[PDB]
Amino acid sequence: MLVLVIGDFHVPHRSAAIPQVFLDRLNTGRIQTVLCTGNLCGKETYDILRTLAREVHVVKGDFDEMQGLNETEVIKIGNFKIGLMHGHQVIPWGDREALAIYQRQLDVDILITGHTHKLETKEVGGKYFLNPGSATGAYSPLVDNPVPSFMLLEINDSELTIYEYTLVDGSVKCERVDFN
């Protein structure tokens, strides 16, 4: 019932590594599921994700060439139907009402998107909108100083806890958000 939410690893022609402190934490997390918003650094990243959990879901980001990734996925965890997509498709970008439109078309309680490279948890009308930011703090035109980040969710029936992990000025920070 622990879910890693992660993505936006890779931007073409730019290098950026996952912090090793993140890898060490997640390899010992007993993660049940990975929900990945896409933009992997090739098979290397997919192998990493497959070591973290038994069940891995990855959607197609705008830089992905890996064959066979779907644009959207819906996954049931606890009492939550969870929609997953990279989010560059949601126009105008990251805009609350456009996101809400996709959340209703996918019939989900939680909508997970990326593309902005800025981690954000937001409850809106009893629906949840989650963005883990970029695991590598990768470049984005939309953000000047992105930081490496990810989310762990703890789901117990209708209980939802989000742990927001970021790497700021060389030190890890975590913020816990509780929803019931």
Image (spheres, rainbow, N blue to C red):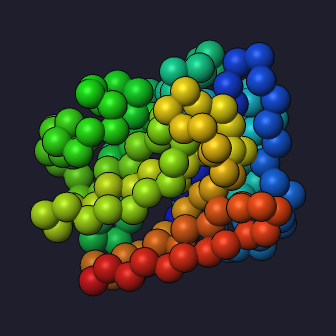
Query: Observer-nearest residue: 165 or 106?
Result: 165
x%, y% of residue 129? Answer: 32, 55
Query: Observer-nearest residue: 149 or 58?
Result: 149
Q: Is residue 174 visible?
A: yes
Task: Give the residue drawn at x 27%, y 83%.
Answer: 180
x%, y% of residue 34? Answer: 57, 54
Task: Give the residue drawn at x 76%, y 54%.
Answer: 51
Task: Give the residue drawn at x 32%, y 62%.
Answer: 122
Number of marks in picture: 0
As displayed, is residue 35 above or below residue 4? above
Image-quadrant location for residue 159: bottom left
Going by the image, does 76 lie left or right of 28? left
x%, y% of residue 121? Answer: 39, 62
Q: Is residue 35 visible?
A: no
Going by the image, does 143 lie left or right of 71? right
x%, y% of residue 103? Answer: 21, 45
Image-quadrant location for residue 175: bottom right
Going by the image, does 144 lie left or right of 95? right
Going by the image, does 162 lie left or right of 79? right
Task: Give the residue drawn at x 23%, y 45%.
Answer: 96
